[PDB]
Amino acid sequence: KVFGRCELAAAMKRHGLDNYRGYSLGNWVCAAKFESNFNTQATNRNTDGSTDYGILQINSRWWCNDGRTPGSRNLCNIPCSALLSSDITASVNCAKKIVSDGNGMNAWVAWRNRCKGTDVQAWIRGCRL
Ligand SMILES: [Cl-]
Ligand SMILES: [Cl-]
Ligand SMILES: [Cl-]
Ligand SMILES: [Cl-]
Ligand SMILES: [Cl-]
Ligand SMILES: [Cl-]
Ligand SMILES: [Cl-]
Ligand SMILES: [Cl-]
Ligand code: NA
Image (tube, rainbow, N blue to C red):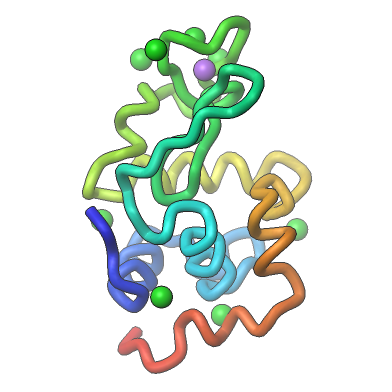
């Protein structure tokens, strides 16, 4: 599923991500935009043989099981395939554990390089929320 901007903002708020660990809704919408262009089925192979899955590009090295990432962990206790669903529950629950890990939203290299410090409120502007 490819979400619209305000549609994803609403689903993220419903699932409790708005202000989670102090990050406003606009930060989470901006991160999804540059990670996946709002497409739940996005995948991207890394140089190290791991893979990033879904609307927030969560990596199989630590967070989910794909059966093909040697020596990896599955800290979210889920198959990576659950991260590609039209229902975002699994992605949001796993993102909560990632953003709690010590480095905040800097865990997402695209949020640090494209969203951090910018006018992130623009991502939720005009949305009926
Ligand atoms: Cl957009
Ligand atoms: Cl915001
Ligand atoms: Cl594996
Ligand atoms: Cl394969
Ligand atoms: Cl594990
Ligand atoms: Cl599994
Ligand atoms: Cl959803
Ligand atoms: Cl923080
Ligand atoms: Na894994």
